[PDB]
Length: 67
Length: 65
Length: 67
Length: 65
Image: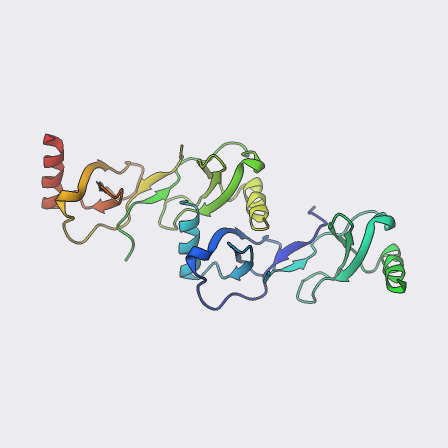
């Protein structure tokens, strides 16, 4: 059982770290997706796919739920 | 402005009302499951099984414009 | 090597699902912590510890990555 | 208004300046590593090794008020 509405997945990861100050939110893509992934939402409301195994990705996450 | 790709992991069980669908598109081949997405006037992206008769018929009607 | 500043960890998980509409952000606690955990930041800016293995927790995360 | 607990996973290598510390507290026993937290006037929470001489001395001075 699962939603029959589309679900976002990532098939590519941004190569280098996004500017930390341009990021306001994040969310992990569904476990249903083929690739694990972190999607950062920038302040201009863009959505960027990132690799959860990357050090900067984990640090950005730790920073985001301090705020 | 998004790097994500919409994929489908379930198909709607019953035929969606034809009257409220404004267009359709097929989910990316990158997605594991093949699927037709019917977009409703309220911008709902509903997943449907490409092999279903009603789905093929809806697509045909949307193709004739 | 690691930050010598304090790092937040969770030692208890909220028993039941928080109201989805009261949540604006989330972040996973450091892998350094003894327990894996998800910290939801409410709109009143409170921080609630949650279990990543819980179904509602994963769903809330998937939802937050969409907004 | 938070359910989290501050823990320490590293100790500051050199003695922090005494002049800018307003208080201290020990991290929870729930944390895996024992630690003293020196809070600076800029609200930085710095982790320090309880066994260090300077740490015990700083604590003593903060205890005499």
